[PDB]
Length: 299
Image (cartoon, rainbow, N blue to C red):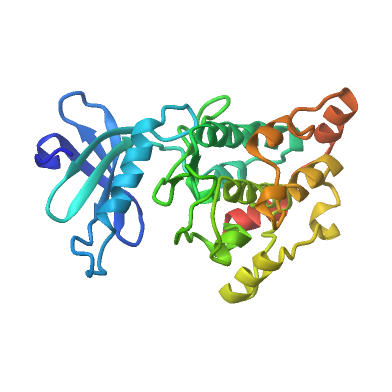
């Protein structure tokens, strides 16, 4: 990587986000005036240290981000590193989370919702085409480039858990957020591209109903709901949801990864690509449960 000082090439501004051993700050490149996001990642530095991120893990993230160029994924611009930190100079995604944005609309049909969902599917299609599992797909890693345009571009971010899947599966850690992680992750079994598809199912479920499907009253119950694939389409939230949409979700929230809809299949699903007008109208007439979705988005 680049061993020079960040601060000789960039000025930094306000913090944008912070993780356990990472902070994102807004920055501006001196030589072009272009603005970026700088993600400072703390290295643990010694293998036995537990106060940072494994440098190998950092390289993995960097290695993946350098390979991807796609409108619905964040771009990597430059990488710096000093004694304590590796700094990723990333594309600045300024528009905030997708769900906060959708939360401001007065209503939302399933057809409009699929317009945004389709962009997520597109990004993931690209990633999966390159054998890349994201492994941390959840509403907060779905951002907008700019919330002030006719049709806003979705940006998939945070590749901190992402892996190349060369052998159809990988046997590792890879544990993200209880609410959105597939059963095989919860149960520490081998992990593949299909984990991402489960996550897509959870996001979709929340997008239409405002409800989290496997959210227990404690974190441990949440993981247990997930493992058992214990979810319902409770009438209180789904009474205005299409059968197509329900069928879409049902084919992703499948315990066996192997049985789960692939990204190629989900892009071909009639909820996503209606094969006839009746299906098209069905999706047009169904609606997002907007008052509960707004409450979820505000949590």
